[PDB]
Each structure stands twice: as structure tokens, then as C-alpha cells.
Picture (cartoon, rainbow, N blue to C red):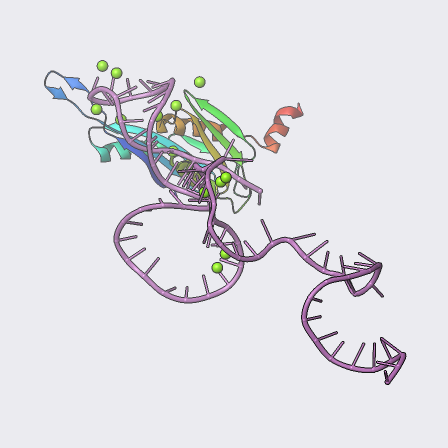
Length: 150
RNA sequence: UGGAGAGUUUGAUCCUGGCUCAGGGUGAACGCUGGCGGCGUGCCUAAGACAUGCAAGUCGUGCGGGCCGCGGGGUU
Ligand SMILES: [Mg+2]
Ligand SMILES: [Mg+2]
Ligand SMILES: [Mg+2]
Ligand SMILES: [Mg+2]
Ligand SMILES: [Mg+2]
Ligand SMILES: [Mg+2]
Ligand SMILES: [Mg+2]
Ligand SMILES: [Mg+2]
Ligand SMILES: [Mg+2]
Ligand SMILES: [Mg+2]
Ligand SMILES: [Mg+2]
Ligand SMILES: [Mg+2]
Ligand SMILES: [Mg+2]
């Protein structure tokens, strides 16, 4: 059903009289490679607990990606903080031309041919968030049609 | 029919921002190594200095000769 991908895991530290106190951050992608993708970022005392928490959170955050012959209905450029993502539609045979973060998402989203580009802050966390916002914003001829029918 | 990023400022974080790496190219050079062939290519520096040979001539159907030679004439 849903395939999970781990974007990254960081160790993060905090301070107390005595020393440092770690936590673990986990960014996890989940999708059915059939138009549904979810992002999840969970943290916990230990990695596993974190990951699991991430996965659990991903499923809580789903996006309905309007796949088309394997690509996206058009181009969007989304800015999440200092990270900017650029998604450009492509023909078949192209493949998923993207950095690891946007890829993992696009792939589990069902996207198969797409032109991508990371601009601004390359921060994986905000890039991944930038992506979901991009996809989430994709519209369709029918969608526009609906909106401008009035 | 066309576009991937990564490492590094912090105890940790986000940002800014420089440095650095992965790719492609070259009339190359250097090191270790070196079997065959085809096609290309080879002073990028002193437009510095050059031994030696060759690199622009040809025409007797424009012309008159010199030199070396043969043949035939005008005479007893
Ligand atoms: Mg770090
Ligand atoms: Mg900005
Ligand atoms: Mg990435
Ligand atoms: Mg930058
Ligand atoms: Mg500082
Ligand atoms: Mg440090
Ligand atoms: Mg501080
Ligand atoms: Mg940088
Ligand atoms: Mg040769
Ligand atoms: Mg030659
Ligand atoms: Mg020269
Ligand atoms: Mg010379
Ligand atoms: Mg000269």
C-alpha cells in the first residue's frame, strides 16, 4: 500500500548543567506511487521511536498529486522560508531529475518524469516542505475549469 | 525533449555568506605503466639566432649568337 522513505535523520543537542542532551529528528516520506504522498517529521529520544513517529505523522499529512502520463500538469515554483523549489513538467523517458529530497517525494508520489531545481537555502527540511507545498498547489484543466466556470 | 546536488561557521537551530568536491573540455605537460591498427594531431616559449640541401620557373612554334661535333656544297 504505502511505501516509506527516510529523507534524513539528525542528532540535535540541548544543554543542561551537566552536559548535552540529544534528541533525534526524522523526515519521512510516504506514498502509494499512485498519486498520494505524505511528509512526516518526528523527533524522539531514540531514532526508531522518531522514525516511527515520523511515519505516523506522514500519513497524517497527505497530498493528492494530479499525475499525468507520469508528470505534473504544469510548472510551479514554491518558496518555503529561504528554500525555493522549482517543478517543471517533462516528457516520458526523462525520469525524475531532482535532488535527493524532492526526488524521494516525487517518486513515492507517483511522479515519473519531471524537471526539478533547488534554489535558495538547500535546507532539506524546508526544501521538502517547499515541495509538498508545490505539489499541493498543482491544479488541473478541470480544476481551473471548475474555478472559472461561474 | 530540457535544469539533481554535497562537505564546512553552532552545544544545538534557522539564515547569511565564502571556500571546497562530484561533471565536461584541452595543440598539453609530468609520474608509474605500456601490445596491435585506422583516422586525426604535434614549438602554446625567443616575430630568438641559423650550417646544409630542396622550396619558381618555363618557352627554339618570338630572336641572334658563342663553344664542342658530324654531313653535304663552290676548286684541279
Ligand atoms: Mg549540522
Ligand atoms: Mg527569500
Ligand atoms: Mg535534496
Ligand atoms: Mg546560499
Ligand atoms: Mg560564529
Ligand atoms: Mg563543531
Ligand atoms: Mg549560542
Ligand atoms: Mg554553503
Ligand atoms: Mg599516424
Ligand atoms: Mg604527420
Ligand atoms: Mg610561434
Ligand atoms: Mg624557434
Ligand atoms: Mg627571425
